[PDB]
Amino acid sequence: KFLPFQQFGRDIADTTDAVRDPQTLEILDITPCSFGGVSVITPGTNTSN
Amino acid sequence: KFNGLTVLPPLLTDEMIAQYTSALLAGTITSGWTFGAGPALQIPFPMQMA
Ligand SMILES: *[C@@H]1O[C@H](CO)[C@@H](O)[C@H](O)[C@H]1NC(C)=O
Image 1 (cartoon, rainbow over the protein chains, first blue to last red):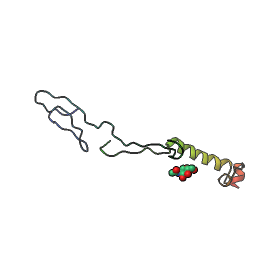
Image 2: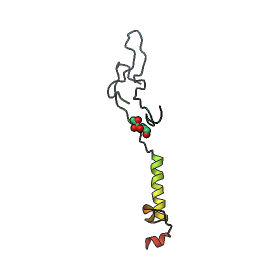
Image 3: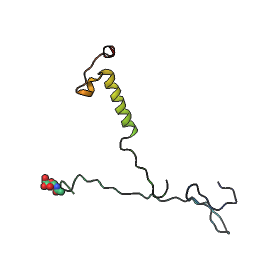
Image 4: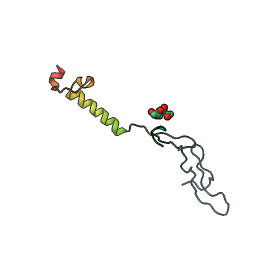
């Protein structure tokens, strides 16, 4: 819930909401979509594959 | 959750650490100091305190 005058929103870097069209507005959250690294388990190349 | 930063959960979770501490307490109460230097040797606690 944002006071009905602001347009952008952020707490550290960016979490902006509200559609910036003068015709209409709609609160849309901003967040990544589960980025991450990948790790591989291997008992050893000279014992299995 | 920010961009580019992630936190790795600890390998040894809370329950296992609690179990380790409980095992240490049980050993030091029911066996004195003999469990840290070989097999656990039972001994009554008043005798261990003396
Ligand atoms: C894997 O095991 C074999 C058989 O003991 C050995 O000859 C080899 O040096 C080991 N290491 C690799 C990288 O193959």
